[PDB]
Image (cartoon, rainbow, N blue to C red; front, top):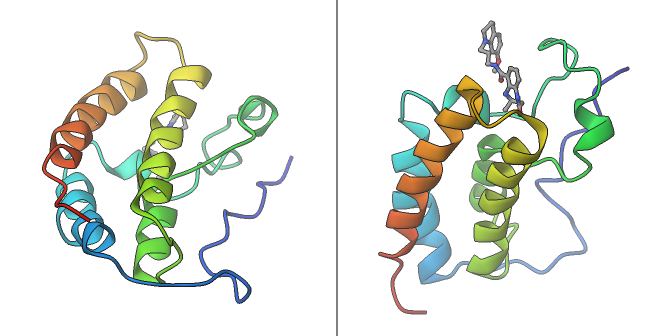
Amino acid sequence: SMNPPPPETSNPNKPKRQTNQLQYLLRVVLKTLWKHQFAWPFQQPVDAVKLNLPDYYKIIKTPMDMGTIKKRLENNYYWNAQECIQDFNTMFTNCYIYNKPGDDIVLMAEALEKLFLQKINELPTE
Ligand SMILES: COc1ccc2c(c1)N(CCCNC(=O)c1cccc3c1N[C@H](C)CC(=O)N3)CCC2
């Protein structure tokens, strides 16, 4: 099977804005996670072809990744911070559904999630 197209990062029919929390998600939260040693697997859509995961898009119908989230923030794709946080949460939940708990990838996601949740606790007032 071919990869699916990636998630949309722009939509000319979706209203756009910047908020204080969206700027914090891009400038602080995403920056902290992106520089982590464990970030690489999560910096772009899951390439199920290159990574030999032929059932990945059979099991995961709501793919999400940090590269898409970055692009969405830079493109002012989100209206609400919660949309952005939901994408991060989807990304971690996919990892927990698809892989065995002991898998290296899951240990890596658990660490990144922990750092995510700490940084979201520091979100400024809307
Ligand atoms: C990122 O691009 C590349 C390109 C080339 C190479 C690598 C990575 N790597 C690093 C490989 C990173 N492995 C994965 O991602 C991965 C592998 C198996 C299963 C999952 C995996 N993780 C995703 C989140 C999907 C997921 O749930 N489970 C090395 C070989 C060369």
